[PDB]
Length: 70
Length: 40
Figure (cartoon, rainbow over the protein chains, first blue to last red):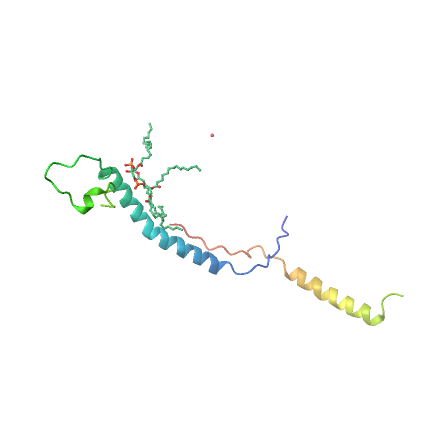
């Protein structure tokens, strides 16, 4: 039945535009960061603890596990 | 008891205007013009 009516409502264009801009920028930075984190974890990370070699002093960044932390 | 003639006249005019406005609230068959675009 063709009895469609007009629904009066406030302009939702600005709110949707702001949400789209937030999502766009947040993803624009997060997606490369997430990809880099995944690649580092799968190809580089997971250091393993070892006893200190005799007479060898480690660097200050050699006492941490995660490669990004190092 | 009941409506005065002024009340009757004002009510009739107001309801005629209200019915005109409510009819104007309807939609034409092409009224929602949607702009198309795509990127078991």
